[PDB]
RNA sequence: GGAUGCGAUCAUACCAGCACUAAGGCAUCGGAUCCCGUCAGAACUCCGAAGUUAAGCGUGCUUGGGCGAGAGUAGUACAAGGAUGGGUGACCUCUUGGGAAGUCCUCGUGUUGCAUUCCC
RNA sequence: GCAGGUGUCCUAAGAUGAGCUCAACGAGAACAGAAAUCUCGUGUGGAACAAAAGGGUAAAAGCUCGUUUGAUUCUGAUUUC
RNA sequence: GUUCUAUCAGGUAAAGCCAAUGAUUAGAGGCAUUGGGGACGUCCUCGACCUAUUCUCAAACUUUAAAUAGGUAGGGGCGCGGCUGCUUCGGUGAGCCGUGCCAUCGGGUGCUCCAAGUGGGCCAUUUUUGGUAAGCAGAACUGGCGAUGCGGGAUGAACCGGAAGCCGGGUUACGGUGCCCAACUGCGCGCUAACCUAGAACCCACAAAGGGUGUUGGUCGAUUAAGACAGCAGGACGGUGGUCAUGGAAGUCGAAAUCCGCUAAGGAGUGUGUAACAACUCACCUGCCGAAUCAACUAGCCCCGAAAAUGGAUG
RNA sequence: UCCGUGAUAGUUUAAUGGUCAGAAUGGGCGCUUGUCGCGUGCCAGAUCGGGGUUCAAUUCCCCGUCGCGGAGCCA
């Protein structure tokens, strides 16, 4: 329903909902969740434990147990992450990783970034940095009481996404 | 095939069970193909339908559905070929015959004592072909109507419940052939 | 074509449907829970409704006293923080002191001593006080209970200040003190236990003295000056106004009013049928043409 | 197998609701409180799971006899068989519906008596109906309650149904 | 003529789409030292007006597919009572009191009770 | 007679309150297929409730979190039996 | 107890659930390997298999809406005054007591004591569930037998009439009126000739799928004195021994193809042929004859299918 | 035909508490030995067919094919 043709912006322009940096490997294969250390450094705040629910067929009977780790960041902290993260995968590159929904994600070792290797006791190769982009009004699908779906009208587009991010430092 | 004669199962008399997910061990259905002829067309080139309609509401045996069809089907191919018009058989074999099977010969037959006693191993199935239902529905083009008519006449000597041939029409073939070209 | 979203709804209609008539407009809007509603309503104590978030929020608050009847609920009194500057006050209408005073204003307004029928003894006013742990006479609460609505039991919080303004207002509302916004948390004086501060009117006072630029008109004591004017006794309002001209009106209302069906569906259908017979391509949603004349009918004639 | 009364056995209206009645019931039914001598249906909402009587009772109309906390006692009489007694049923107001028939009736009674007063100060119809009412001694009721609950232990249907 | 709170009727109250509570009778919105909270004010929440009408809340319309309700169009199924009524029979039938159904047209993209009460 | 369950298992698999709302599908994430995980959008009872069937319920009765002990003693009008 | 309200059996179209199985149109996207190509100084496209989604034809659980139908439920008021309650030293009614006032049936009927066979049924009708079925088994709802005469059904526990003190007379019910046997060899009309056939119901009275130019009857189409239908009789040259195919068609194994000159009529032919070659009839047309004909639907009865045991019957 | 009773690798035959399966022989590979054999190190199962219950079934139910035992009167 994209209504652009008016007299526009400041509510329309994109913002960062979140950056989630998530590891998926498992326990035992590298450790407890020790690339939490590496997350800890790159992002700047502590990652939180990922448990699983549902199926595996492959070892992974324990269910409730540590297997993964994540950092959902946002404000300045997400952006500050983007700046370092944004520059490492090369550019430019590419429409395919963007969804139509207007989010984009990439992989690489935590060791990419400025950072000491020396502090991370382990490095671990890859897992999604995910960037959630959205308009101001999101708060309607998010907030509890008066949830309303986000309309086609509101929802970010890959074109819109590429533009706002391509606007900045890549 | 191995005997039980169909009169016993002819009457619409007992409660209707066709439920496959509870009724375990249910054997092969038939007819092997229900609509016979083309299948590159639907009704188009065939501006005549002929039907066989039941006078008598009854349970018709699964093999009788094949037997009535096969006599009709050779008349179709032996007088109008492989990829001709299209016939449809339109009542199908819902009614699972459980019913006493496998008798023995002591002073037991009924093996446990005399009993017998449901959880019977299944024998076959019948179709409920009720009054005025269209058992066979055949779309044809007019010169070959008389060919479908002998084929329906051969069909009726091979099920129990008496039927009449009719050239079938809903909106004629003469409100269709107006209403078609009035809204284009 | 493909396509998602619509298609996974329009087929599974019957489900839809059910989703809109399981609950109605205040739940569809997402406003009122009908399990908290039932907890609080069954007894005839009235609902002491105090809204404050995704509603009226970050700007004003309201307290309403609601009873049941055959027609619908029925508010017996209400107070809005926007009426609170009438009694002199001009500092912020969303804060703890505003909420506190808005609850007194509803509570003073509900007795106000009404109707022939009266009631101001044993002992309304319980002053604009300062306060300690609820002094009543004293043991049984009735004719108001707190309907927090969507708003939380979050320990030491502004819904409780509204509740405290009810209590020091001559309403008696049920209580025990173990998540509550106690005494100084309006401001008042305080404090005890595992929860903390021992200031909160007087919030902003602590802040303001940590220097920086913000709102005009001073300081910590300006809570005290016009909490003190809201300690005075002075029922009741609202209001005197001139009524009302003719008619309705309004330029917004007008460029919206009124009706138009039938006729307008007939003008639009005429436009559609003329648009078809002058071209023939697609209809409205989504397909057909060869060659039509409205509506369900056209599709049946384009098969055979 | 002996017969019983599987208290939960055969239940499709008695617990299912139409498409139009599905989902949570609005709490106004849960809130509704009645006065003694109200005539109220018993007929469960199926979408409330507690406070229900034993399912056979549903579609009978009872008199509100007394109340205990939250649920109410409503008096009903069982039906069919032999010598059957009044029984009292404990039911919350979620399954108990006010009789509109009884309200309509109450109204139709007042209408009748507005006219009785008018037509006895300047009007004429009946005469004979004026002769009973005016005499009577009244009143309420429990002699005639025991009178009610002795022929509804019915007579000839009991012998008729007592063999076949 | 009506937006803002609490609700009744809970498939006439939808999915979808187009105008509007609004220069001092909202929500988006800004500060997050804070009570509160999170992993992370995003939610949550003390605080609060610079912007916005762009929404949400909700207001004028759109029946489009959905359906309540009804109008014609399918008296057809079905069934209660009764027949030395018919039929070899499964079965039918008259009489007595009753009678869904699909299509098309239609109405309908709310209604109602208490509030705060408002621009004209 | 058809169809199929209970003779266990549970101090949390109870209680309450705040706070949340699905299953699932598409789209996105180097590697992973079982791949969880992490995200977004759509999402009304199709999920979830130990256990048959069945029926029920969406700020819940379901989810999450803390706390708690009422699986306390004694009495019972009445329904089932 | 009809009328008011409730809500409910119930099972067809639709919805969720699910559907065997076969009959599928349009059209997006999965997967796999292979093949082909222009476009341009790889791309992109196409093809070989699967699934969305538009979606037709047919039963099956739940729900609509049942329609239904029986069920099945139900048929005093006011004021005054005291006292009370639950739920803010807070709002209210309700309860209670006291006192006054004002208001289509028709004994089908309540309570108590003490006693009985039981505490094993049957059948019919309706609705069923099992069972091939059964004078089966097992329920539901009812009427009867049991425990019910008398009259009809040849006889006959439960079908019909009918519920009975005894007797007398009258009239009837069911059912019947040729004789046996009271009472019609009744009236108007029509069908059947098989001794069909003398029969509601019955373990008891059989008769089917299917067939029948027997006969009657109803209807519709076409053909008719611009002469029909049938029969009998009579006319048909030439292209050219029709093109294919094949020992061979050549009218006449099989398969093109079916026109015309010359004509008033006159088809490249209807059945009979010899290994193959050998003739006759016939399409169409005409006469003779003179009146209805033919086609087709529908229906009745009858006929057929129709074989069993000591001796023939609808009593 | 009724009541009882079993089955696990090529073959004969152990075993469990619901989360874990063996042995011996036979056989497949080396070494003995001139060569085989005697002997000596090494190795290797859809627990009968079948469906169900459960967090997890070789193990707990139900059915069946086979192989067993034990009954079957008064004619």
Image (cartoon, coloured by chain):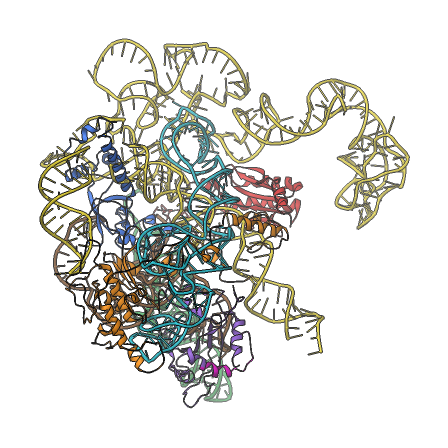
Chain colours: A purple, B red, C orange, D blue, E cyan, F brown, G yellow, H green
| Residue D32 visible from this viewpoint | yes
* Residue furthest out toward the front: C242
In the image shown, does B11 or F69 lie closer to the viewer?
A: F69
Q: Residue at x 31, y 79 (%)?
A: C207
How far across and down, in percent of the image, does residue C119 sit? 18, 58
Image quarter of residue G102: top left
Where are the magenta residues, as a range?
A80-97
Q: Is residue G218 depicted above or below G82 in this figure?
A: above
Frontmost residue, C19 versus C94: C94
Q: Is residue D62 above or below residue E28?
A: above
The residue lying toward the viewer, choosing from C302 and B109, is C302
Q: Is residue G260 above or below residue G181?
A: below
Verify whether residue A87 appears in magenta. yes
**Residue at the spot x=44%, y=64% of the render?**
A149
Quadrant location of residue C187? bottom left
List x then y, in percent, for residue B92.
50, 47
Quadrant of the rendered image containing residue C229 = bottom left
List x then y, in percent, for residue F57: 34, 57
Locate residue G82 relative to residue H44 in the image: left or right: left
- From the viewer's perspective, is A40 left or right of D59? right
Q: Is residue D106 above or below residue E94?
A: below
Percent of width and height locating residue H68 = 35, 60
Residue A42 lies within the magenta run: no
Q: Quadrant of the N terminus of chain C?
A: bottom right
Marks counted in the figure total: 0
Q: Residue at x 27, y 66 (%)?
A: C87
For residue D100, side relative to residue D137 (left or right): right
């Amino acid at each position: 329903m994209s209504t652009e043709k008016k007299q526009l912006n400041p509510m329309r322009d994109i913002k960062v909902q979140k950056l989630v940096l998530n590891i998926s490997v498992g326990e035992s294969g590298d450790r407890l969740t020790r690339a939490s250390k590496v997350l800890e450094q790159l992002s700047g705040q502590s990652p939180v434990f990922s448990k699983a629910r549902y199926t595996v067929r492959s070892f992974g009977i324990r269910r409730n147990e540590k297997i993964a780790c994540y950092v959902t960041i946002r404000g300045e902290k997400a952006m500050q992450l983007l700046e370092s993260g944004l520059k490492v995968k090369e550019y430019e590159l590419l429409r395919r990783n963007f969804s139509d929904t207007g989010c984009f994600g990439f992989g690489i070792q935590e060791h990419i970034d400025l950072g000491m290797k020396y502090d991370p006791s382990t490095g671990i190769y890859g897992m999604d940095f995910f960037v959630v982009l959205e308009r101001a009004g999101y708060r309607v699908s998010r907030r509890r009481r008066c949830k309303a779906r986000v309309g086609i009208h509101q929802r970010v587009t890959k074109e819109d996404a590429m533009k706002w991010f391509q606007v900045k430092y890549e | 095939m191995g005997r039980r004669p169909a009169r016993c199962y002819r009457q619409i008399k007992n409660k209707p069970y066709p439920k496959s997910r509870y009724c375990r061990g249910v054997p092969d259905p038939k007819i092997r193909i229900y609509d016979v002829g083309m299948k590159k067309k639907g009704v188009d080139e065939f501006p005549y339908c002929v039907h066989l309609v039941s006078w008598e509401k009854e349970n018709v045996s699964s093999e009788a559905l094949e037997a009535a069809r096969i006599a009709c089907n050779k008349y179709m191919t032996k007088n109008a070929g492989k990829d001709a018009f299209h016939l449809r058989v339109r009542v199908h074999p819902f009614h699972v015959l459980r019913i006493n099977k496998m008798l023995s010969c002591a002073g037991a037959d009924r093996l446990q004592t005399g009993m017998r006693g449901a959880f019977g191993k299944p024998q076959g199935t019948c179709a409920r072909v009720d009054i005025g239902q269209v058992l066979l529905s055949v779309r044809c083009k007019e010169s070959n109507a008389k060919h479908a008519e002998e084929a329906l006449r051969r069909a009726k000597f091979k099920f129990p419940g008496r039927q009449k041939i009719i050239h079938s029409r809903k909106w004629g073939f003469t409100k269709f052939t107006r209403e078609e070209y009035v809204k284009l | 074509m493909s396509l998602q979203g619509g298609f996974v709804k329009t087929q599974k209609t019957h489900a839809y449907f059910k989703r809109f008539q399981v609950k109605f407009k205040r739940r569809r809007q997402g406003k009122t829970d009908y399990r908290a509603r039932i907890r609080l309503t069954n007894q005839d104590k009235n609902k002491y409704n105090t809204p404050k978030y995704r509603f009226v929020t970050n700007k004003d608050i309201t307290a309403q006293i609601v009873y049941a009847t055959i027609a619908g609920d029925i508010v017996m009194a209400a107070a809005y923080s926007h009426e609170l500057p009438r009694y002199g006050l001009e500092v912020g209408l969303t804060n703890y002191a505003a909420a506190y005073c808005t609850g007194l204003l509803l509570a003073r307004r509900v007795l106000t001593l009404r109707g022939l029928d009266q009631e101001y003894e044993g002992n309304v006013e319980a002053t604009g006080e300062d306060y300690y742990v609820e002094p009543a006479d004293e043991r049984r609460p009735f004719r108001a209970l707190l309907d927090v609505g969507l708003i939380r039991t979050t320990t030491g919080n502004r819904v409780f200040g509204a509740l405290k303004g009810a209590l020091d207002g001559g309403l008696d509302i049920p209580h025990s003190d173990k998540r509550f916004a106690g005494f100084k948390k309006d401001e008042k004086q305080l404090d005890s236990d595992i929860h903390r501060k021992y200031i909160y009117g007087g919030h902003v006072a602590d802040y303001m003295r940590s220097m920086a630029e913000e709102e005009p008109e001073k300081f910590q004591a300006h809570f005290s000056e016009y909490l003190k004017k809201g300690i005075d006794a002075d029922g009741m309002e609202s209001l005197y106004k001139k009524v009302h001209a003719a008619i309705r009106a309004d330029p917004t209302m007008a460029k919206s009013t009124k009706k138009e069906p039938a006729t307008h569906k007939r003008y639009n259908l005429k436009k559609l049928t003329y648009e078809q017979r002058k071209a023939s391509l697609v209809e409205r949603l989504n397909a057909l043409n060869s060659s039509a004349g409205a509506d369900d009918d056209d599709e049946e004639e384009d098969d055979e | 197998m002996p017969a019983g009364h599987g208290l939960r056995s055969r239940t499709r209206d008695l617990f299912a609701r139409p498409f139009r009645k599905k989902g949570y019931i609005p709490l106004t039914t849960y809130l509704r409180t009645y006065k003694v001598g109200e005539h109220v249906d018993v007929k469960v909402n199926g979408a409330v799971h507690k406070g229900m009587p034993h399912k056979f009772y549903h579609g009978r109309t009872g008199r509100v006899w007394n109340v205990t906390k939250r649920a109410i006692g409503v008096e009903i009489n069982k039906q069919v068989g032999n010598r059957i007694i009044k029984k009292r049923i404990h039911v919350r107001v979620e399954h108990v519906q006010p009789s509109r028939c009884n309200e309509e009736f109450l109204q139709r009674k007042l209408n009748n008596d507005k006219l009785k007063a008018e037509a006895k100060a300047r009007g004429e119809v009946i005469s004979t109906k004026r002769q009973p009412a005016g005499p009577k001694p009244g009143f309420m009721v429990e002699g005639t309650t025991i009178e009610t609950v002795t022929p509804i232990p019915y007579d000839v249907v009991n012998d008729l149904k007592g063999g076949y």
